[PDB]
Length: 134
Length: 134
Ligand SMILES: [Zn+2]
Ligand SMILES: [Zn+2]
Ligand SMILES: [Zn+2]
Ligand SMILES: [Zn+2]
Ligand SMILES: [Zn+2]
Ligand SMILES: [Zn+2]
Image (tube, rainbow over all chains, first blue to last red; front, top):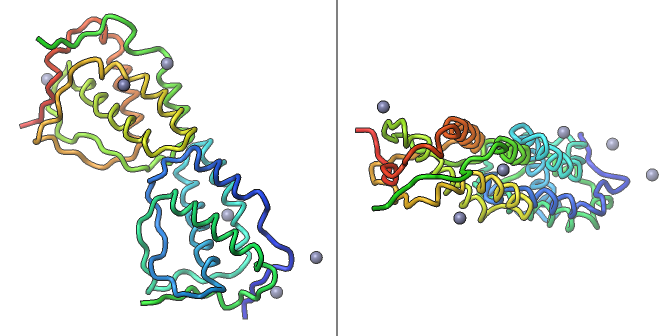
């Protein structure tokens, strides 16, 4: 079974800085998406969204200018650890809804904060399969 | 009667610079619009489009990060001369279409180049009213 756990915490302490820096050069209502029906799971929840947010940082880098690429990539690095785990592609039941990139960035920050005290204490093996709610 | 002429330095020599400096920090496919059926007019064509690109620059300034505002505010200053004339509100016939902001900025640059050799020699009074193709 693919496992997923972090012995040492992957979250850096100045991640909120790299996000405020990206936001300083962003057109805040740029359309991105967020899952609208992610199952309520107090252990995998933030992790699922970080994986999704992470998938967005990559897509954004491809249509970003030389200098915006660095700000994206630098925020990408703060949450790229989620790929250390074999997360499965989103299920067909997962619905996405258009939201401002400022919303996505704000939530990502929040998820890192809430995840910080637990990232190294929990076994996240069952988070690999993203789950839906109706 | 309302007049629209420019006897000063309307278009500068360094506009492609403030623009490229803006694009380097942009998500190239950010959604904007361009008029799709602007009537054919040798004298007003570019001006009308600059008029529209200008309103976008103002708009995008209200949703931009503190530092993106500066990048914008400077590109807006390059085409700010269009607000010197009493351009009338766009006609109901004027259809708009979504386009990447990269295409808008590229076109805005091309327009300033084409308009540069003439902006201070022509009288644009008849451009105050934007027209559509039949
Ligand atoms: Zn292992
Ligand atoms: Zn160790
Ligand atoms: Zn990567
Ligand atoms: Zn200039
Ligand atoms: Zn003609
Ligand atoms: Zn003004």
